[PDB]
Amino acid sequence: SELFSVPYFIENLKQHIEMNQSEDKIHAMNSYYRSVVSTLVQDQLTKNAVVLKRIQHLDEAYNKVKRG
Amino acid sequence: ELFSVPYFIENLKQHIEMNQSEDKIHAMNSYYRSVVSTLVQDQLTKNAVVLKRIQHLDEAYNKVKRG
């Protein structure tokens, strides 16, 4: 719900997995992960603390989705 | 030297070669995810420094991928 939050990334990670049925679930997650981090880290407008927190959110979303 | 671009380029290549179940691109993504996770768990390095390490990793990734 909240922009760039854990549930936000959990939702996106789940949908990305569902949209790529010709790739391994874990690999689809890592692809989405690399692309998101790359975009966030290239952001020269958002505060470092905010950008880092967003990556932390994505990371937690990844760990949660992986368990399920 | 640590967590620098050349550093990640070297380690990316080592994982790609040592890995026995993932091809080039898949190995890079798995290495990347695993490293960023660690770097993000860092609770004693300044946030600016942490991001800078992740930026170098991304730059190394982009270089090894197009190269």
Image (cartoon, coloured by chain):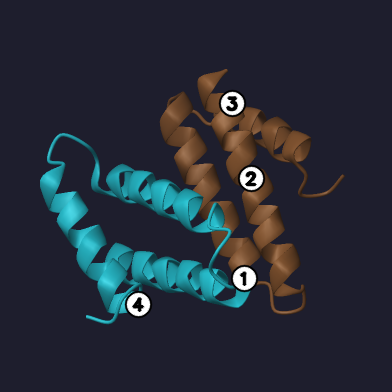
Chain colours: A cyan, B brown
**Amino acid type of the residue that numbered disc 1 sits on in the rendered structure:** Asn
Q: Secondary structure at mark 3?
A: helix
Alpha carbon of mark 3 to alpha carbon of mark 2: how far?
10 Å
Alpha carbon of mark 1 to alpha carbon of mark 2: how far?
16 Å
**Amino acid type of the residue that numbered disc 4 sits on in the rendered structure:** Ser
Rendering coords of residue B60 (x, y %): 64, 35
Most extreme residue toward the front, as rendered?
Answer: A45
Residue that mark 2 sits on: B57
Q: Chain of mark 4?
A: A
Instruction: Say above or below: A6 vs B2.
Output: below
**Amino acid type of the residue that numbered disc 3 sits on in the rendered structure:** Val
Rendering coords of residue A53 (x, y %): 51, 75
Residue that mark 1 sits on: A48
Residue that mark 3 sits on: B64
Crowd rating for badge 3 (residues with CA inside 10 Å; few <14, some 14–19, many 20+): some
Which quadrant is the C terminus of chain B positioned in? top right
Q: Secondary structure at mark 4?
A: loop
Q: Chain of mark 2?
A: B
Most extreme residue toward the top, as rendered?
Answer: B67
Q: Secondary structure at mark 1?
A: helix
Alpha carbon of mark 1 to alpha carbon of mark 4: how far?
16 Å
Residue that mark 4 sits on: A5
Left or right: B7, with A30 as reference point: right
Left or right: B33, with A10 as reference point: right
Instruction: Say above or below: B45 vs B36.
Output: below
